[PDB]
């Protein structure tokens, strides 16, 4: 409920991760893949576990290719041709806040090579992965957020132009959110493209919530009204037009951070309710042992990559929601 | 002390700061001045107290002038016409790692108006402070470091050019390190210019050790061997040519952070020894209650501004030394 309780829940999960961290810096995943620990540097840093976060940086650095990518180890389909750069985005942010300026420069440089200069979006499928050059809202939003942390504001602005075009070009937003555009910049409505079923409870809301977070952060960076209006449009869209699952599904953390940030920037109490309700909902789902999981309930020493990623992820969202609610209350009182 | 123990000493100092933080976000200083808490955002964030760090950001934001400076409250002469930008530099870094991108952009924008475009140095005295346009190695090094964290690498490279020219232009480096150049870039040997007596135990060593830290981070950011060679020439200068006080004085933490950083990058055991020794020395000076002080020993509720600055400063240095020694160990195992 309170920002102190969100933070305490995050510190427990971070303690759970650090106790089971491997000597090479990898987090306790049942499959050694990058999609199990890409949020690890940033998450452990915000929890104060700077030597554990630096150890993850040691692990990430040893996997780095000369071009700045980490193409292996990757197994999950979503980290191959859905949002390949989703891992690279958190890696860039986590490295930069740690002061690993060489790691973050190389990571962000590769992210830039995947930018579509015509549209501002970022390619969904990595190198040597079959695909048609499509660009999705998640790859674009996380790369734009990585652009903000590394000071590449023009890249972040161009990424917001993509999200603005993707929002206006929606053919039927009341029923479906097409989160992908083709290489020319047109909204991609192909069956094999990510499309959120908005009036239904089938998840994938972070294709809307992560753009809402990134756009609010970009507004804070620039105080350009257009980025605020688009972020509030996405929040209104998720609150009124979308199913109740938009703030219940496991991917609702992005929108919760966006609402917490929007509360500190605007003071509108509806954003505090969305942030508090989401942050509370993640606290209730936490295992007493510290981790989050879909199936596991016992005192396990490792998790499958999806649960381990979600655990480090909720460390970030609970910490971000907590400090923006705490500061928003101080500001607007 | 091991890296685990340096981090434990940092967490205790951060804990001490957080319990006494004022409702407005200010740290427990007996005088309300910016020089008492400018390292607060960065230090509290690295310790994991992200809500306390956000609170410092709110307090700092309430002081920010439209041009991005915080000229008041200031009282210490060193933050007026010796190294005025020393406070702004840590504020920029702390704001940026927190994701307060509006605060960090505005702070960095002002810092860059203080850059001398002909020399790459940053003016020692602030606006409306009497001065002649001199630039010092501390204002330049902390501004270059803030530029690295905000991703303005051209500014950092220019700051490095100033440090290299200041180093080559030393008229008597074995006796005195003149840390100040004039507006045209000539090394300033006037009596009113900062000058370190390198063969006496008279402090002010951070005019050499903070350039060494920044230049090491710039080398990590660019892998331009010129910045490594200059950083190593400054460490060798402090190790062999300079008095033992360069690694014992309260301002030695900068040299220790540079040594820890150089150990992870180069693996040379001498750098690990400098960082270990400086790290354990600061741990031994810590009070039982968690703060650092020059002459205070009781269970106090606040501190002299210089003691509070030192307390937040040793949170940073002990954490940075600890994480770089631990990661250097893993890398050079």
Image (spheres, coloured by chain):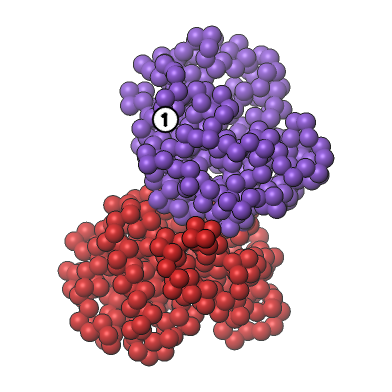
Chain colours: A purple, B red
Picture quadrant of residue B125: bottom left
- Of A55 and A63, nearer the camera is A63
Q: Going 65% across and 40% down the picture, which residue do you hit? A: A29
Picture mark count: 1
Q: Going 38% across and 56% down the picture, which residue do you hit? A: B220
Q: Few, some or many C-alpha atoms within 10 Å of disc 1 (few <14, some 14-19, many ≥20)?
A: many
Q: Is residue A47 visible?
A: yes
Q: Position of residue B183 (x, y in %)?
A: 20, 69
Residue occupied by mark 1: A159
Name the secondary structure under disc 1: helix
Q: Going 44% across and 85% down the picture, which residue do you hit? A: B245
Say above or below: B145 vs B302. above
Q: Position of residue A323 (x, y in %)?
A: 63, 48
User: Chain letter of disc 1?
Assistant: A
Picture quadrant of residue B265: bottom left
Q: Position of residue B89 (x, y in %)?
A: 41, 62
Q: Going 38% across and 29% down the picture, which residue do you hit? A: A115
Q: Is residue A333 visible?
A: no
Left or right: A272, with B268 as reference point: right
Left or right: B179, with B16 as reference point: left
Say above or below: B100 vs A205. below
Say above or below: A92 vs A165. below
Q: Position of residue B4 (x, y in %)?
A: 63, 65
Q: Residue furthest bottom?
A: B200
- Of B248 and B59, nearer the camera is B248
Q: Quadrant of the N terminus of chain B?
A: bottom right
- Of A235 and A133, nearer the camera is A133
């Amino acid at each position: 409920n309170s920002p102190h309780e969100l933070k305490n829940a995050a510190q427990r999960a971070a303690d759970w991760l650090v106790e089971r961290q491997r000597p090479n810096g990898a987090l306790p995943s049942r499959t050694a893949v990058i999609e199990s620990c890409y949020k690890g540097m940033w998450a452990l840093h915000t929890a104060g576990h700077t030597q554990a976060a630096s150890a993850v940086a040691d692990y990430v650095t040893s996997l780095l290719q000369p071009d700045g990518d980490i193409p292996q180890p990757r197994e999950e389909r979503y980290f191959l041709d859905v949002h390949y750069l989703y891992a690279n985005g958190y890696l860039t942010i986590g490295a930069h806040v740690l002061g690993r300026f060489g790691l973050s420069r190389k990571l962000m440089s590769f992210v830039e090579t995947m930018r579509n200069p015509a549209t501002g979006g970022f390619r969904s499928h990595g190198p040597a992965i079959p695909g048609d050059g499509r660009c999705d809202s998640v790859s674009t939003s996380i790369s734009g957020l990585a652009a903000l942390y590394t000071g590449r504001v023009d890249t972040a602005r161009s990424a917001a132009d993509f999200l603005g075009s993707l929002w206006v070009g929606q053919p039927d937003r009341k029923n479906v959110f097409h989160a992908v555009a083709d290489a020319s910049g047109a909204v991609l409505t192909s069956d094999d493209a990510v499309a959120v079923q908005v009036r239904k409870a089938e998840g994938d809301w972070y294709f809307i919530g992560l753009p809402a977070f990134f756009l609010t952060a970009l507004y804070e960076a620039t105080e350009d009204r257009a980025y605020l209006d688009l972020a509030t449009d996405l929040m209104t869209y998720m609150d009124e037009d979308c199913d109740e699952d938009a703030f219940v599904d496991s991917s609702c953390g992005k929108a919760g951070v966006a609402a917490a940030l929007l509360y500190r920037l605007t003071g509108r109490p509806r954003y505090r309710e969305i942030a508090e309700g989401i942050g509370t909902l993640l606290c209730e789902r936490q295992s007493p042992y510290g981790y989050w999981s879909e199936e596991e309930t016992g005192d396990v020493a490792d998790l499958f990559w999806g649960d381990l990623d979600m655990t480090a992820e909720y460390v970030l969202w609970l910490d971000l929601i907590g400090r923006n609610l705490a500061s928003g209350e101080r500001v607007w009182a």
